[PDB]
Length: 153
Image 1 (cartoon, one colour):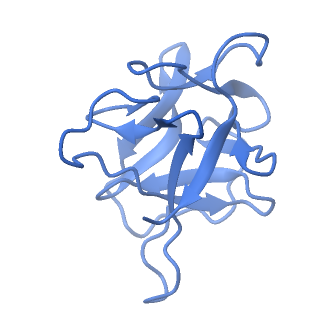
Image 2 (spheres, one colour):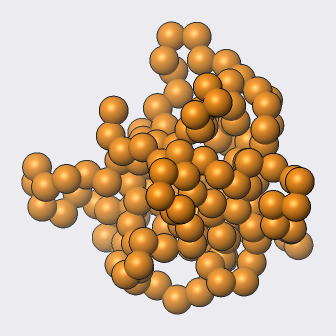
């Protein structure tokens, strides 16, 4: 999540998929898993990745100022693209609250911790219909917390 800064100096545009012919992609309000629907490339998964110091912090852009955060739905909290209506306030480091992620990249594939140290846990749906999921339990036969990390187009 960066408001331009230096001109022509590397935009951090990020995309996520997996080697079993599966991809992450936004339709209206959620990043769908594996392979649902994409008729003539009307999706655009490019998000700006900003780190605290060792890779972990937050995500933002998806067309025009949509911030990927751990949002509060009363008692529950899931991954959401909230519309940020301010170009001046953009966090470089930030403290532990329901808004960051620990990106645990084990060489070619990662996992997403939520809030940051406490909060919610790293997975995504297995087949072509449900989305990205910050769950209540680890990988004890649950979902896909082993997904490949790709940059730009």
